[PDB]
Length: 234
Length: 225
Ligand SMILES: [Ca+2]
Ligand SMILES: [K+]
Image (cartoon, rainbow over all chains, first blue to last red; front, top):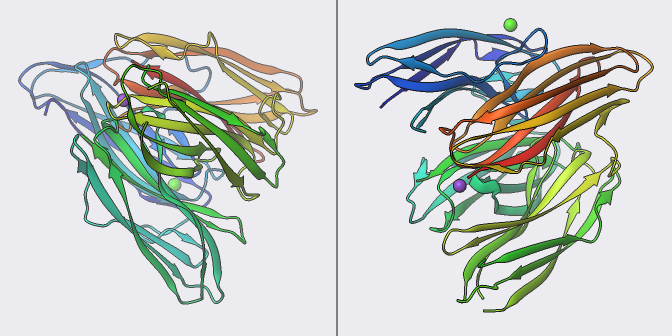
């Protein structure tokens, strides 16, 4: 409630040769007192890519500086970034992030895609990957909870697909919790491999953000595609 | 404390075609009372690779020690580069214990990461692994040495991937055209403000050769208490 952040991108679909995205950042203080904070814009992408929105002509020497907003006041700022051709095709998340002086974190995220269609299933050349938080459960209590995920791999290819599949939960304190062991499946042409797999968040697991991360590999082509979903343990 | 975790790899260097790594897992309870915990074995690798090697198992152990060996295959298709194997234990009381070991695939252990003759030497300058909750500053040395016959056209940046989905800029994107035999050399630090959340930050550095399109990352951990 101290801060409300908002983000819009000028476009959300880029070709494989990349392009330029401009963004509008809004940070509003809806509180009764002045709020001091730091903020930045960062991008997460495929193949473990993380990069800041900011690019400099020479040596980056800046510090992460605070700003402050009087009660009822807002900041409206504009930022752009190039997405080079060399960066992996796939799904990217742009994240406006604000850390208030009191430690509260506020985020506003938007996605864009590069060389794949927007709102189209991640795929490995006709083998389509549909992994979903089954009941839309975005968080669990500190005392523990369980979250099931549906996994549907549709083989739209003319021939059979040989895939390897696994899942982990990448969490606070460097944790990488197994969710689904490595499995190898042979999927006939026109078949869909379906299963449901859940993770139990034991009471003892640390509070914070967990990325449920599914990886699918075509064992013949060696190509790999990921799907990530977030669950917060309160 | 309640748990000591130990990890040993039988081998730390695979060729590009990969192979088999056998792990020795040691977990000892050397506190006064008996201890309940869950443990597992997972691997982190280049290009956002994370994969399990051993499922979550709950154990109710003391001066007792648990000893298990567990193996895993690293297939050819996985990226060449540096991997970390992590034996992870969470005690009932919420304390987390990790024992990590690295292996490489398709690159030499004890050689610098490189992009075809351009070497990338990025280090936590003073080996500072953690900072106080009230804040601290950690400097990193960056040395990109062009040992090639011609120019290297490179792009460089850094972030701190931290708790609460944070991705804190550490070094904005820089572009350098480095002459044969020249170096790009700097020290870049990150100030962890008091306000930043407690937990693990991965200082993630990337270097790209713009011409080949090849990218190397270097990841380094700092914990804010
Ligand atoms: Ca464009
Ligand atoms: K934590």
